[PDB]
Amino acid sequence: PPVKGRATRQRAAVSAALQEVEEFRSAQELHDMLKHKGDAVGLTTVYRTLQSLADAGEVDVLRTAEGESVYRRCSTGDHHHHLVCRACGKAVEVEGPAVEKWAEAIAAEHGYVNVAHTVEIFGTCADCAGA
Amino acid sequence: PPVKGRATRQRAAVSAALQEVEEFRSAQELHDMLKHKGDAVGLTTVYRTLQSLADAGEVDVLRTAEGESVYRRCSTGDHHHHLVCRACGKAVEVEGPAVEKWAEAIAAEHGYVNVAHTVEIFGTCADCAGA
Ligand SMILES: [Zn+2]
Ligand SMILES: [Zn+2]
Ligand SMILES: [Zn+2]
Ligand SMILES: [Zn+2]
Ligand SMILES: [Zn+2]
Ligand SMILES: [Zn+2]
């Protein structure tokens, strides 16, 4: 995950920590995990670098139900949607043409110039039922 | 939008305000319009009434880009989605069984028990582009 800014240990450390974790997590959780790992990196720095990465498109953003924001890194660069288990926090990426075709048809019917569709869905996975 | 508790002039006033308009708006925005027209109702009061209505489902909820939740008393009561223009605030009731079938199929394939899809499309009207 290259960063537009100059090469520094902060950007490399946060990028590596994000790569290690494969779960949607908030900025505070990321900062706490980085502190536990010994990075000793600032929360405000985490916020700025994370916003820069989100603007760069190398990372996947998501908004929590209560209002906070979680973020995750997905290997695929192509456009995709997310299934996120709130109980576990695990996220899996998928892609289905149906949403794209429906969005295009709706835009054509209503004459909208450009549209931006967000499809991030939630559901409990099997392990939650298991005890 | 009937309320579970005893009807009062404040609850009736906020209900009248909700049914008066059709665009999405937050508590502060609805409160501002009610204060201007001469209702003189409280902030936390309208917050509580809107939380109760959303619990009952009489109104429809939506988290904006910033995160704050805007609301709309929608005419149609069945399952539906909304196409929203941020520049205008108009909401168009659009429903498609294709997305529901896709969500059910992916949930079954992944073995997920329940699916709670969060789907929204943001766009701009043709008039918006024109000047
Ligand atoms: Zn992804
Ligand atoms: Zn899509
Ligand atoms: Zn789970
Ligand atoms: Zn509606
Ligand atoms: Zn639906
Ligand atoms: Zn518009």
Image (cartoon, coloured by chain):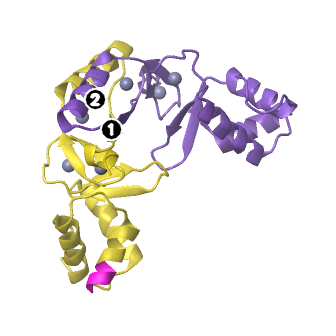
Chain colours: A purple, B yellow
Return the mark for residue A103. Answer: 2
The range drawn in magenta is: B34-38
Q: Secondary structure at mark 2?
A: helix
Question: Are discs 2 and 1 less than 8 Å apart at CB?
Answer: yes
The residue that label 1 is drawn on is: B121
Return the mark for residue A17. Answer: none
Q: Residue at x 58, y 28 (%)?
A: A57
Q: Residue at x 22, y 77 (%)?
A: B13
Q: Is residue B23 left or right of residue B76?
A: right
Q: Is mark 2 within 8 Å of ligand 2?
A: yes
The chain carrying label 2 is A
Q: Residue at x 31, y 16 (%)?
A: A97
Disc 2 marks which amino acid?
Ala
Magenta stretch contains residue B35 = yes
Principal SS element in the magenta part? helix
Disc 1 marks which amino acid?
Ile
